[PDB]
Image (cartoon, helix red, strand yellow):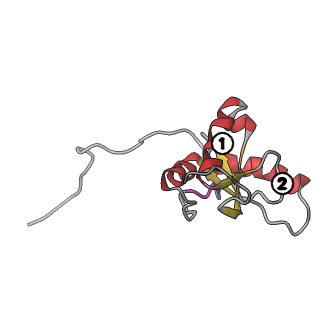
């Protein structure tokens, strides 16, 4: 409380890493330092240690695209880091501790859709049929 020393992050097992083309060179620092103060280890360069990746304004699928690059320059057996959004981080910082990842956080896709967007629905006066009695 009074002193100001540091050696081993509170949660070393969890290493959060941000993206340049996703966070920026200036902004990155903002969180980079903020987290460190809370109790999170920020990695400068993409390293196997990286367990969680922080992406801002990234689509569930988009994240994956950037994840591929890892497996490309990553060693065998090494498990890929869980791609999450800024929401997760923010919630963590405000909590002082790394919250447990959740579906919403996980950034993944599957069986995507295609085509334009339109209602193509029917109005109220779009019902008919015979009757008796």
The secondary structure making up most of the magenta span is loop
| Image quadrant occupied by the C terminus | bottom left
Mark nearest the camera among 2 and 1 is 1
Q: What residue is at 68 percent from the left and 46 percent from the top?
A: 62
Residue occupied by mark 2: 47
Residue occupied by mark 1: 33
The relative height of residue 129 versus residue 78 in the rendered view (above or below) is above
Estimate the x, y position of residue 5 in percent, counting from the top left: 68, 52
The relative height of residue 31 versus residue 112 in the rendered view (above or below) is above
Question: With 25 as the anchor, is 104 left or right in this view?
Answer: left
Estimate the x, y position of residue 17 in percent, counting from the top left: 72, 49
Which numbered disc, 2 or 1, marks the residue that appears first in the sequence? Answer: 1
Q: What residue is at 65 percent from the left and 62 percent from the top?
A: 10
| Image quadrant occupied by the N terminus | bottom right
Estimate the x, y position of residue 105 in percent, counting from the top left: 57, 56
Q: Check the image and name the residue furthest to the front.
A: 2
Q: Which mark is residue 61?
A: none
CA separation in Å, label 2 and label 1:
18 Å
User: Within the magenta stretch, is there residue 1?
Assistant: no
Q: What residue is at 76 percent from the left and 57 percent from the top?
A: 50
**Secondary structure under the numbered disc 2 in the rendered image:** loop
Crowd around label 2: few <14 · some 14–19 · many ≥20 (10 Å): some
Question: With 61 as the anchor, is 65 left or right in this view?
Answer: right
Estimate the x, y position of residue 52 in percent, counting from the top left: 69, 57
Q: Which range of residues does the magenta coloring cover?
A: 105-109
Please identify the quarter of the rendering in which residue 28 is found.
top right
């Amino acid at each position: 409380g009074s002193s100001g020393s540091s050696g081993s992050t509170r949660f070393p097992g969890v290493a959060i890493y941000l993206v340049e083309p996703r966070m920026g060179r200036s902004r990155r620092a903002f969180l980079t330092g903020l987290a460190r103060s809370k109790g999170f280890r920020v990695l400068d360069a993409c390293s196997s240690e990286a367990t969680h990746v922080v992406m801002e304004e990234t689509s569930a699928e988009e994240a994956v695209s950037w994840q591929e690059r890892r497996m490309a320059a990553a060693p065998p057996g090494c498990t890929p880091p869980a791609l999450l959004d800024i929401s997760w981080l923010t919630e963590s910082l405000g909590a002082g501790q790394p919250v447990p990842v959740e579906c919403r956080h996980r950034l993944e896709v599957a069986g995507p859709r295609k085509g334009p967007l339109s209602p193509a629905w029917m109005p109220a006066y779009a019902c008919s049929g015979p009757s008796s009695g």
